[PDB]
Length: 493
Ligand SMILES: *[C@@H]1O[C@H](CO)[C@@H](O[C@@H]2O[C@H](CO)[C@@H](O[C@@H]3O[C@H](CO)[C@@H](O)[C@H](O)[C@@H]3O)[C@H](O)[C@H]2NC(C)=O)[C@H](O)[C@H]1NC(C)=O
Ligand SMILES: C[N+](C)(C)CCO
Image 1: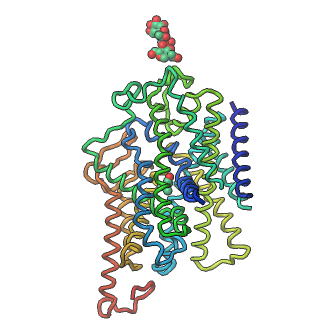
Image 2: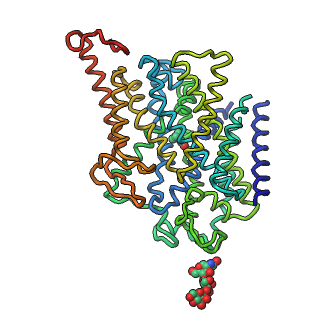
Image 3: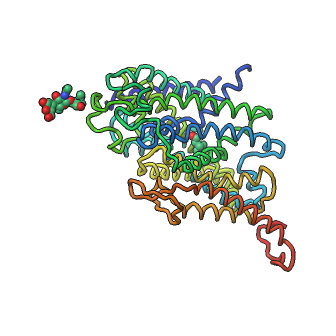
């Protein structure tokens, strides 16, 4: 087990690194490579393992696999709406507009939650990589994720002293070659039948009841409008040369990620349609055994022959471990540059960049490892990433950019209001019992209250209206008498 798995992973990762450095070593297609790399930024660890877990779990089903359909629509909306009002004014990055208007220091306050979201995303990628490595070499869960994160961070440290194209071909081959003949054991039932009638378990095409349609709408408008303000997307859009180039790139990336989500949904459907008693996985199912994150690696390993399995599985592991470096490097470099050019100053010649980036990558590897080492989900961390980005970035990025009005006062007021209406609202994925108990609450199996009434969307709306109202009242009273203009720290007058 151990030796063959290590051989496969080492061989395939060495090959992909050689191919990448060779392509870097030395027309009518240019958009397609850009589309592939931009959809390579989203895919990797997030979709495949995450959406496999979302489909497989009895209770979620496909109807609650909110992410893969959420983020393609996120790209479409972001391109079609924000692609135009991002060129004429002139924006180096998405961090620049916040520092341009809200004095400059408030950018760090606004990008501590985006940093937290990217921490969550890195934790999801690390958990996916740990799951795949643990399945392929059969050593353990907690050790595997720590080792994988250590390798990823060490590779980040010296990896800077085109790859993304080969990375997606690795995923596309690895999955689509392993499930034209995977649903062929005497165990796997008809993928069409277990969608609507339930052989081994409750149907993988999950059902949403009329009582909790509001939760669906909220948790789907969350993903749609929280996948847009991410740093990687706006870093790729602004470097695009032509105006319509950004729109075309976003549309092709959305189509690519929709096509890429197909091989992973069927994997979850197979996993939910098997008979985990005639295979080699023993009597317990991966549902009454908290290993629902490994559904995709388990179906790839056990429901495929020896030679077909490890090719695709090693390809998937290599692709996700490749994406880990991009995640960590962005999450460290953006923080270092923005906030240590924000706070006072630091000598950027030979000290600031080197040691602050080094300490940042070390601490972020440690934090992502600790964050993904305890939460036994791979979809939950990803969802919470998009969640917090939605709550406390999208309203302010929408009011600063789309039309007009946002002062600094409204920024802090909306920040406080949104954070309050969430942290008092309740986070079921973590062990955070709510404190307001919005009408329609139903207790969960664990013992953690979750709410049917929407409070993420309510938090977004409250933050936006708080920003607008506070800023316009500031424009009302910028004169004397009512709060004389002497008080001025961050100015709107
Ligand atoms: C998969 O599950 C099936 C049952 O759904 C298992 O098949 C049955 O397993 C039992 C226990 O090993 C075999 O012994 C039988 O036990 C009952 C208990 O009262 C006894 O009354 C019978 O006289 C018999 O001794 C049983 O023969 C077997 N049935 C068949 C048709 O093979 C099976 O072991 C599970 N695992 C697989 C298929 O890998
Ligand atoms: C929505 N995110 C950008 C956080 C991940 C896409 O997989």
